[PDB]
Image (cartoon, coloured by chain):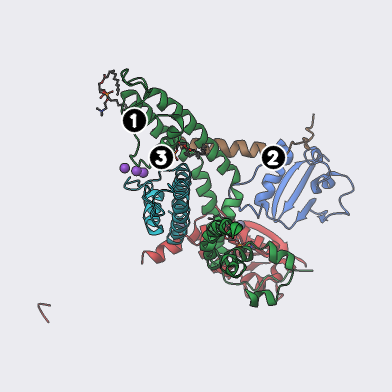
Chain colours: A red, B green, C blue, D brown, E cyan
């Protein structure tokens, strides 16, 4: 009862409940609790929760849960990863300085670029 | 300075601090008025040279800037590229100085007793000066070739200077860009609270 | 008994024991030995060892074991790898 | 810029090969 | 950052060139500097800007070996401290 399998867009991500329980308040934290069958999508035949999201970036979200440091995958756009971690509940101001300038780049650019005869 | 001397923990590092050294060297000449005949003239002549450092007190203020700390780290971390640049410049200067000195003597008039009378390149060290001024694309115009061979040598000097200056400077600039970007990132990012409470 | 399945964060990586046994002293080297059921996490129903790590970079670690040259994946930060 | 990029690549690779300590070939290849 | 770098470089090199050009000063003339364009420091500021920007008008230039060394250092440091933030 210590292992939990997340099915994210058809890719099975497996982990311990302690790992999810590290970061509280986020969605996966609510997953780790014992009252999660009713709250979330879940099928008892395979004992997997199903989330209809990109799995390739959920790898890095779960890596944040495991190791403790948030990094940005260099193989997806900044806005894509931003929206994904926005969905998962992760705060965007936690990414490490090594990958902060490339992450917060397009958003910086976008914010900088933005009586009858009368 | 006296108020700072009042509290001086780790006096060894306080004396090793270059800022306080600069302060003391800059404050020495004025305070030497009461101390200050034959040796006095020599020590005053050197006291003017010491007072020359009085401009170095601006680093006391500018140390708190971020860009200057980044520049210091870049300089300290890019010594190899500076050595490469100085070697390239020395080789180019020597070679082109010799070449221009010998080129300007082909068209020398036989009448004058001296080897070179109509050319600014009367010797090689003048060639060093001209080679620096021409490779840095500065081009003061105080001395320039006046012979077709000299003009060919000058064109080659300008091109080779552009190239041998643009070789390592991009490496140094990339180092500074990386350091400045990282420092600005670390300065912008608000202080974290460590949301992730690690498991035992 | 020559094949071994590593389950790294839910992704099954399969390899021969010789491949793991190439580089000695490392963790996977200890995996390749026959006294590995007790030392490491292992379930006999699927015959897989489970490690709770990023799988995408374990691909490259295992590629080091296979080929013999260590490379860095250009799709993850330096500190992560 | 093309010439400078060539020199930058070559210099980076040469400094990498010079810095890296001599390896001992940890990976003993299987027969 | 650029304006700070330029101000520091200009001040330092102006002082350096003004003091360098006085080493080779002739003792005969009553004034401190008669044969050099660097009669004071603000002229040094102007020359330092013109030389660090690789402009090189040629209205004023060093005429002493120490002045020439200072000028070469000024040109190189100007190239570097301009190519840093640009
Ligand atoms: C002209 C040649 C003489 C220049 C003397 C340099 C004076 C100096 O040391 O400035 C240092 C600062 C950066 O030094 P910092 O470490 O950030 O400040 C603390 C001072 N320490 C800890 C060293 C005691 O500032 C710098 O390093 C700026 C580099 C200046 C390059 C021109
Ligand atoms: C291009 C190929 C150029 C090849 C030139 C070879 C010419 C060889 C002819 C030998 C005899 C030439 C001669 O006797 O004089 C003809 C003129 C006069 O030249 P001068 O008498 O030696 O002195 C001129 C100096 N002024 C007048 C300005 C004060 O001489 C001249 O005015 C010629 C000067 C032009 C050379 C400058 C070349 C600049 C770079 C070349 C292109 C570089 C491409 C990169
Ligand atoms: C390279 C190392 C160079 C070291 C030079 C140190 C020489 C020290 C000798 C002291 C006595 C020199 C002397 O009394 O005069 C010898 C000549 C004449 O120099 P001057 O009398 O002071 O004035 C010359 C000005 N003209 C003639 C153009 C109007 O003096 C000269 O013509 C020498 C001028 C050459 C110095 C320019 C160096 C340019 C940069 C150096 C390389 C930088 C590399 C980056
Ligand atoms: K120029
Ligand atoms: K110019
Ligand atoms: K000019
Ligand atoms: Zn995109
Ligand atoms: Zn990172």
Chain ID at mark 3: B
The C terminus of chain B - image quarter: bottom right
Q: Is residue A53 visible?
A: no
Q: Which residue is mark 1?
A: B145
- Left or right: where B187 falls relative to B146: right
Chain ID at mark 1: B
- At 43% across and 34% down in the image, what residue appears? B126
Q: Nearer the viewer, residue A111 or E26?
A: E26
Could you say which disc has been placed on residue B133 in the image? 3
First in sequence: mark 1 or mark 3? 3
Disc 1 is placed on an element classified as: loop
- Disc 1/disc 2 C-alpha distance (Å): 48 Å
Q: Nearer the viewer, residue E31 or B111?
A: E31
Q: Residue furthest front?
A: B37
How many residues crowd mark 1 within 10 Å: few (<14), some (14–19), many (20+)? many
Q: Quadrant of ligand 6?
A: top left
Q: Nearer the viewer, mark 1 or mark 2?
A: 1
Disc 2 is placed on an element classified as: loop
Compared with residue A115, is residue D23 higher up or lower down, i.e. above or below?
above
Q: Nearer the viewer, mark 3 or mark 2?
A: 3
Q: Are marks 3 and 2 in contact (CB under 8 Å)?
A: no
């Amino acid at each position: 009862s210590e292992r939990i399998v997340i099915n994210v867009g058809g890719t099975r991500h497996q982990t311990h409940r302690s790992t999810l329980r590290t970061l509280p308040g986020t969605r996966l934290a609510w997953l780790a609790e014992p009252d999660a069958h009713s709250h979330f999508d879940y099928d008892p035949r395979a004992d997997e929760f199903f989330f209809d999201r990109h799995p390739g970036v959920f790898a890095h979200i779960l890596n944040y849960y495991r190791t403790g440091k948030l990094h940005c995958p260099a193989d997806v756009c900044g806005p894509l990863y931003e929206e994904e971690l926005a969905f998962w509940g992760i705060d965007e101001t936690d990414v490490e300085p090594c990958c902060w300038m490339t992450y917060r780049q397009h958003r910086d650019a976008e914010e900088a670029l933005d009586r009858r005869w009368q | 300075f006296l108020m700072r001397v009042i509290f001086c923990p780790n006096k060894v590092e306080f004396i090793k601090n270059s800022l306080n050294i600069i302060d003391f060297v800059a404050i020495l000449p004025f305070y030497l008025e009461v101390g200050l005949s034959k040796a006095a003239k020599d020590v005053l002549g050197f006291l003017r040279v010491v007072r020359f450092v009085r401009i170095l007190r601006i680093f006391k203020l500018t140390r708190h800037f971020v860009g200057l700390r980044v520049l210091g780290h870049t300089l300290r971390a890019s010594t190899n590229e500076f050595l490469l640049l100085i070697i390239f410049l020395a080789l180019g200067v020597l070679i082109f100085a010799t070449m221009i000195y010998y080129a300007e003597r082909i068209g020398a008039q036989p009448n004058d007793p001296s080897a070179s009378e109509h050319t600014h390149f009367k010797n090689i060290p003048i060639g060093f000066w001209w080679a620096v001024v021409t490779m840095t694309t500065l081009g003061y115009g105080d001395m320039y070739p006046q012979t077709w061979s000299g003009m060919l040598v000058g064109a080659l000097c300008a091109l080779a200077g552009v190239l041998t200056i643009a070789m390592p400077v991009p490496v140094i600039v990339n180092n500074f860009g990386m350091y400045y970007s990282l420092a600005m990132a670390k300065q912008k990012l608000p202080k974290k609270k460590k949301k992730h409470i690690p498991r035992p």
